Image (cartoon, rainbow, N blue to C red):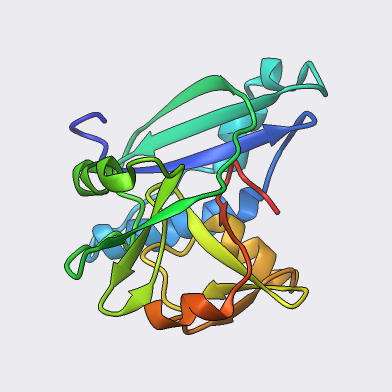
Length: 194
């Protein structure tokens, strides 16, 4: 939440390794450059911050969620245990004016959109005719034996980035009208892989 840290990163520890760390570092720097333009910053080394909490790796079993909230010159690390969660149903929510192109710690709108999920497990934000993100992650849609993700999401997820880099998913423009074409919907994010 906190007032003076307006951005964050959520990192998974799984099987005693921090995951997709360089993807997080990239977004972190991209974010510093967009949010603090004209400033000359020294970015933190996110891998080093994590690594030095050696207690995070004592055990191979278990999942840990590490959140790093930051601003232009400081950060806070917080670690919680995590249990796998299942997201299977998604409520379409219509919202044409929402910017979540960085991972802002102020998530008031996203949280208000999520309240519209009713009986679904989560939401699916339709912005300007296009399927974008759910409230906590990006979305993937099954077609044939492939997984397709929207080429214009609200936020470029780290998990999405790794999956694209590995060719495990495919980027494509997805209009709301296109949902017809797909067989299954799922979420992806730092805590929810494929």
